[PDB]
Length: 474
Ligand SMILES: O=c1ccn([C@@H]2O[C@H](COP(=O)(O)OP(=O)(O)O)[C@@H](O)[C@H]2O)c(=O)[nH]1
Image 1 (spheres, rainbow, N blue to C red):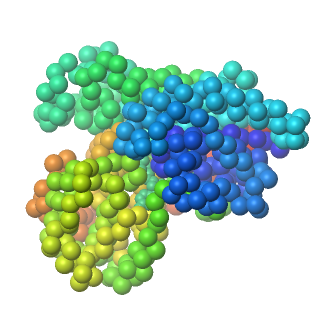
Image 2 (cartoon, rainbow, N blue to C red):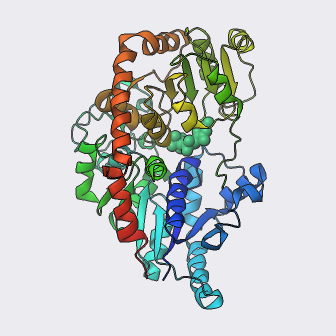
């Protein structure tokens, strides 16, 4: 009997990517896969890339099905409106997904399809677990960010109990001294501060969507058959050991993409710029500052101007991925100093890039990052030190660990100012600060390679979760 796994990501590229990595692996191991897109995600992909690029090839098509479910969302909802996305999905997708499961069951007799044997839901997509449980189908959840981020979200309830959420004083939401307050009660992260908690706690609304949804997600995941985390156990040991008491068995599989690599579908609305890698070929080893802020976050025009002036004054060539909609508001031209550097060939601004390959390019010496988890996994595998500017969600938690525990990064202030940007980049490129972080980055690169090669800790967890849970139906 062919196992049949249904996978359900949240509609953001950092959630689709790890679940698609897993789906491709399961297909390689002989499973039937059904990959479930929301209509929001699917229609936005089709209008950007066309159906042919988004759907599977005819070679894999027999055992790789794409299905689309209703979500009630306008395609105009932007990726930075996380609460709007989360609220519609949790309210609107359950009954469409229940109907999809029924249809897949009818296809067993109708077309000799394999019965569904497991659902793998993104922790965010709690309806997937609810529907699987109703139907008597095992379900295993996949949290797509860091273990430290999960630990933060797990303690949102305790923030509420201690009166810290919602914020009773709106003036404290951005009070840097208040946000520095230590929270000494988080197991596995004794150095947690209020600002290090994932940022959605910073709300005065007692009915805030993201706090409510996080509580639902934690309760859902606690009831799953198992939990997949795309992280390196060695990197996050203290946090994972603290998480163990609150969840089903945890499998640390990170970096999953590297486990697969050791041993045909476009998931992005953006086109990766092919000129990046050849431009880097023309630059000396370790010389280039690479800047990228992921697929969801936005910044202000003033922040963008200060980053641009900081890059022009930092002393290094740079590759800046400036996503086309990253800046709130009307288009503002880049400063003359940066444009002249681009014209001289010393800098390059592109809309989107092949990120894993860019980070592994010998010319890159530093990653200025928003601290999105997939980006940090890509930097960790590449051995690139990180200068952090966390934006939302668990990016703050990641930044705290980068700085204080993992040791492969340093942080910029939230309020971007060109002079301080240039100075911190310079310290990271030629200073003792950068030497320390780059050396630690090299250690984590070796650790990630050991974990991902055959016999390593992440490799073993991939084999166990795949063979003992995901492919075992039949
Ligand atoms: O120029 C870029 C920047 C990002 N990414 C991909 O977009 C995702 C970003 O996910 P992450 O978790 O880092 O952050 P998020 O986008 O969720 O904030 C990852 O798969 C990256 O490899 C990409 O393909 N090209």
